């Protein structure tokens, strides 16, 4: 999915805009907006993270996909559900914001790619089995 890709960029742009940073490096609309409020709702409710997750990752430009993958896997240690996909997306957002705080802005489009790879590979199967983003919208939107 180029579609999945678009979700990722839209989510991460939203978070970057929201938190006072640039987003320059860059039904659908209903999915997008539902995911936008879902992360906000998950971040307010938690403040839990990222945790030793971003902690666990300490991203640099020498970081490769596989390390990202290894960390994000801890989220899905009990398999997938809608909440953990919310957290996966909020996770990506936090990692973009840290990247920019460390003056590592190049990473932002990289992190976006990883997220889209990880999504399309490990998450799309479960998502498709449980009703697609339609259901995500029935439950969140």
Image: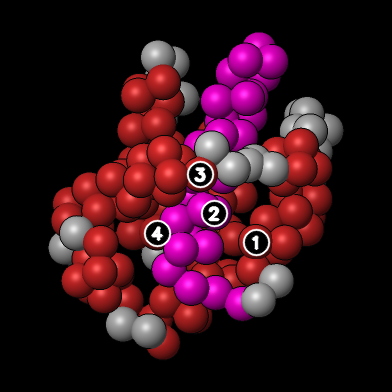
Q: Give the residue at x 55% y 25%.
A: 97
The image position of residue 7, as x and y in percent, is: 36, 51
> Does label 1 or label 4 sit earlier along the sequence?
4
Q: Residues within 10 Å of mark 4 (few under 14, many from 20)?
A: some
Q: Is residue 99 magenta?
A: yes
Q: Which residues are magenta?
A: 79-107
Quadrant placement of the N terminus: bottom left
Does label 3 or label 2 sit earlier along the sequence? Answer: 3
Q: Residues within 10 Å of mark 2 (few under 14, many from 20)?
A: many
CB under 8 Å between discs 3 and 2: no
Is 99 in front, or is 6?
99
- What is the distance, in whole Å, between disc 2 and disc 1 at their CAs? 7 Å
Label whose residue precedes the other's in the sequence (2 or 1): 1
Q: Which residue in the rendered view is the most extreme toward the bottom?
A: 129
Looking at the image, is 77 positioned above or below residue 131?
A: above
Mark nearer the viewer, 4 or 3? 3
Point 43% across, 45% down: residue: 45
Residue that badge 2 annotates: 88
């Amino acid at each position: 999915s180029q579609s999945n890709r678009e979700l990722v960029v839209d989510f991460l742009s939203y978070k970057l805009s929201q938190k006072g940073y640039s987003w320059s490096q860059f039904p659908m609309a209903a999915v997008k907006q539902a995911l936008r409020e879902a992360g906000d709702e998950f971040e307010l409710r938690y403040r839990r993270a990222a945790s030793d997750l971003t902690s666990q990752l300490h991203i640099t430009p020498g970081t490769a996909y596989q390390s990202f993958e290894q960390v994000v896997n801890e989220l899905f240690r009990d398999g997938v559900n809608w909440g953990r996909i919310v957290a996966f997306f909020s996770f990506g957002g936090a990692l973009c914001v840290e990247s920019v705080d460390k003056e590592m802005q190049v990473l932002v489009s990289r992190i976006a790619s990883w997220m889209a790879t990880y999504l399309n590979d490990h998450l799309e199967p479960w998502i498709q089995e449980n009703g697609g983003w339609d259901t995500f919208v029935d439950l969140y939107g």
